[PDB]
Image (spheres, rainbow, N blue to C red):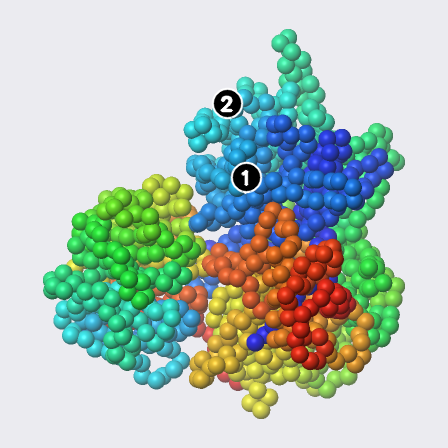
Amino acid sequence: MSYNYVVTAQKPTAVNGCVTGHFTSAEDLNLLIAKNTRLEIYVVTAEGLRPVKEVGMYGKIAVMELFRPKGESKDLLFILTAKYNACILEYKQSGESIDIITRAHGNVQDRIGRPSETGIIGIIDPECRMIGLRLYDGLFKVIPLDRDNKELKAFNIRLEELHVIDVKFLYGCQAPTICFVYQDPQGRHVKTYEVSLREKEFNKGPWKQENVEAEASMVIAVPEPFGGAIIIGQESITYHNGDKYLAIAPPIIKQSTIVCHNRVDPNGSRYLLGDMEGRLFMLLLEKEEQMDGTVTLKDLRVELLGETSIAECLTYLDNGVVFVGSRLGDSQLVKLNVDSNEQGSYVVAMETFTNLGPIVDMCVVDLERQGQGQLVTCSGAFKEGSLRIIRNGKLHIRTVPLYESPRKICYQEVSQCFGVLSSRIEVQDTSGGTTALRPSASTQALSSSVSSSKLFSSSTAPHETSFGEEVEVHNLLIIDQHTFEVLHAHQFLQNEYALSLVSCKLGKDPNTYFIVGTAMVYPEEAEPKQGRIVVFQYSDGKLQTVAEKEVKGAVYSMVEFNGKLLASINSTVRLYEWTTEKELRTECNHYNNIMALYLKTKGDFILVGDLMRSVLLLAYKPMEGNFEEIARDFNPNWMSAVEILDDDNFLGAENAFNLFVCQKDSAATTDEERQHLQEVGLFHLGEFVNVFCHGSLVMQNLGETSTPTQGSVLFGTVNGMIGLVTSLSESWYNLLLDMQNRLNKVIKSVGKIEHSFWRSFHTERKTEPATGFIDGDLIESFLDISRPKMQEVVANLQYDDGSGMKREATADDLIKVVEELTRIH
Amino acid sequence: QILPPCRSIVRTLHQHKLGRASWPSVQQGLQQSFLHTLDSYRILQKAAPFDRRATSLAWHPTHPSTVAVGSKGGDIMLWNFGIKDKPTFIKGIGAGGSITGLKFNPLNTNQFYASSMEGTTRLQDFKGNILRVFASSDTINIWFCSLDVSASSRMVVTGDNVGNVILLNMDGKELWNLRMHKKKVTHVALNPCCDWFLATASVDQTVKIWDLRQVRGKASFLYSLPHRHPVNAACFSPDGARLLTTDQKSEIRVYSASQWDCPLGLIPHPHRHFQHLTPIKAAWHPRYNLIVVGRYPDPNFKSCTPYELRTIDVFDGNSGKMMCQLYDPESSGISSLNEFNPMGDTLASAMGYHILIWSQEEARTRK
């Protein structure tokens, strides 16, 4: 009875993986880039990047590696999805036609199994004897690369080592051989096995297990002539090859964990390394000759090259050029020079590419023109952190760098400014407290005001701090809406994390306040026992504290409610009145939740989304001054965000990348039955939704009755994807679903994945087909196929044009429908 | 006692909002949070008695506060909380008609399956009407002991006191009754994520994994796991990848997807079998990797703890060691059966002649 339409407004921009190779031709150097569901293929030139093809896949790309079987003239591509769809693809070009051919495809799901902690890892041996996949703890899946294995049939080999951190195939082995790091109660170790396809089993590896550093975390497979393996840890770098053992402990790398690597020289003589602070190092292998003509490793050195965006992945191109693929900040093309600059860096940036993800919060404001909505997102992390301002006219994006992590955003029209909660990392100083690693918004304000709050300074046992502990400093920033200058930064109390932010009026008081919900964070506490709601007033260029409320929990969420304050505090939902004396006073409480993380409201009704009990519907009863439990969704879902579609329809998103829609049970004949919400909509989105918000970026057609959709709620994701949810009538739902089925019969799926499988609701507890949701991306894909394919799609299709009787649809009818649909976002 | 927990909780949630930290680490942190709040279940909420001993327990799948229970004398009870409508009852012969297997009907919640000492695997309403019998001994002194059901497959399975198992459809259609064991079948269960391999346990000190569609040849089984003593329960995970097993003398075993033969860990814990006591059944928690069992002290069991009380113990699955213990005087019986809610906010315990409800307290002050 609830029918909804979901469509992508901005595709994900974060890069999850990148590889280079010879995919489009043996002579071409290609770059392939994965942005979750999207695969982009470029040709690498002397000046930069030439786009050649962009495709979507029906899956979250988890592994992407190029390989070239015997007898093939160019690289093939292996892709694995999050739902375990595996495929081998080959690039075929003729004229202006670009096709992704499916050479092989199959589903590699096991009937049972627990996905591993460090996730799916997939690697292909350099001689293409087999593909190896670490999908589940305690199991190693092997796909033999036989010419006949077009279905990617696999077998499992037991792994004695139940907790694998990383694994690689080694180079220079006469039998396929894996090398991996694992953890047990005795510590971490590195071990090898040969993989016998003949025996379908492991055999003893060519070199014995070795002990490694306690935090050894990555394996690099070094090519010939060295062979062997490099093990990267937090404090050390070691090389192993047979009777060869070499370790270094350069102190410079200890400040930040190396998290990615990429080979620079074909012989392994140089590697790039990137750390969590965006520092970029070169690792250089110096050779030693031997009488028998083999080459061995003589020594290892690390050299700091400079700074990049915090890199998820790196690929060296040519001529000193590196592609830096980032998920937390902008991606880049950078140039490496032989000589350093004045500040000692060898790296020079050539080009920067926008990444909007993660979207941690957002709001819609009419910044420039009435009726012209613009989206303002909290984007990024640490030094890459930013605000992003998105407006149409495809899209114009203004970037405001903050150099620290944003968390929440609100708009305050009366002050012509934004409030933004942010956090920065500091490390211990020589003699005192902590010091920041770089300037950021909260340290570069025109003026600043420390939190001198003494709400509970008395009678509060202070908790010690160990010398060496790093600290997070949280701030509320006030930022001008016109200049985007940082007008003010307010620092919160020590160990106090600011979690939620709203701008609103309360009660009968005409002033507008900034209200912040916090938690006091101590390392040994399983859940916070202390927090604050703080009401600030912004006047005369500073925030003055107007009121505080101390609570015994984390204030996860707050929302303005009819001039009152609704707040969620650990396992309680509480309604506060704003008194004549400018204090918060409890009006009423509701207790039957585990953890109320997300609130949205409409009228006197309250929708509470729980971490684990997923959603509950309460009504505040103004004639009783208390809460009433109306209904609950008794199906468990692990929530990440919630939204009220209308008084009767509740939208949820959960951590396994599914959406669902709940309604009251219309066919309920008892109060108890009326208390059960029914999950009437289900859809695998494939993104982790952090936030829904009502609004739209499309020009409003004031008086546009008779359109296919009603309402507009945007949502933001970790990957920088922005989507839109809107409501549909039953007849539109039925028409669009018919269109979906017909599109699914005509569209060539990369890897031959069925749309119904992709969109099917999927958690470790249950798998079910999607219901109640139209895939706007699928509908829009009608517009990029050829006219004859369009004519195929609409053959023998009954369609009601305008108001009247149903008749046969032509391609132009559905072209018009879909074109109209493209303007809703 | 131990219960130490620590972590940077909210950080991880925001880390999950950034994509940095993986979901299983989140599941672990919130598992710890669940343990921390389970430390406040100490205040026992409700108690409920009736006549002859408790033998079987079951949860209303959709509803948290509803529960069904079956006695040693075929006396069934259905009870809901926050209702106060004087719960529903049905009596039986009272002497030799012990209900011993009890699962709800996935279709009609006002129905229920049952396995009885009378020799009658039946489908019956809580108002008394027998809807349909599924099988029968047709000869007294030969009766059933085990029962389970699956909705995705629409199948029923039940086990005997001699060593043969029966498998029916929801509408009859019996293609089964081959012999599997030499002695009584104590417990049996189907996979929830699969539909066509089964698990059965017996007094024969062996627990067997079958493939109900492939095998038809009288112990042409798929796997057979041995034990040192007879087995009272072998229960599947919700996820489907972990099989938990609990014997009669002193042991619990975790078998994996990965090489069913070999076990991943042994959890020693005292649940010593006894004649007039209801047999003990360890159980999973539906949404974490925890294990929950009732304790029965033995002066001969090699106790790691120096304090051995009768209490509800809660262990971690993929490690082997313990994480929590619930205890309450005025309830000094031995919790034979214990089952958490499918919802995840409530626990039911079946002791001899008593049923206990353990949920959290709060509501400091009404307004």
Quadrant assignment, res B184? bottom left
- Mark 2 lies on residue: A206
In the image: residue A640, left or right of residue A399: left
Ranked by sequence position, the earlier of labels 1 and 2 is: 1
Q: In this orientation, which residue lies closer to the viewer: A318 or A291? A: A318
CA gap between label 1 and label 2 equals: 31 Å
In the image: residue A713, left or right of residue B322: right
**In the rendered image of this protein, does residue A266 appear above or below residue A106?**
above
Disc 1 crowd rating (10 Å Cα; few below 14, some 14-19, many 20+) is some
Q: Tell which subunit mark 1 falls on.
A: A
Q: Position of residue A246 (x, y in %)?
A: 61, 23
Residue in the picture at 82% in, 31% down:
A319
Q: Tell which subunit mark 2 falls on.
A: A
**In the rendered image of this protein, does residue B174 appear above or below residue A281?**
below
Quarter of the image for the N terminus of chain A: give it. bottom right
**Callout 1: helix, strand or loop?**
loop
**Callout 2: helix, strand or loop?**
loop
Q: In this orientation, which residue lies closer to the viewer: B67 or A51? A: A51
The amino acid type of the residue labelled 1 equals Lys
- Mark 1 lies on residue: A150
- The label nearer to you, 1 versus 2, is 1
In the image: residue A318, left or right of residue B281: right
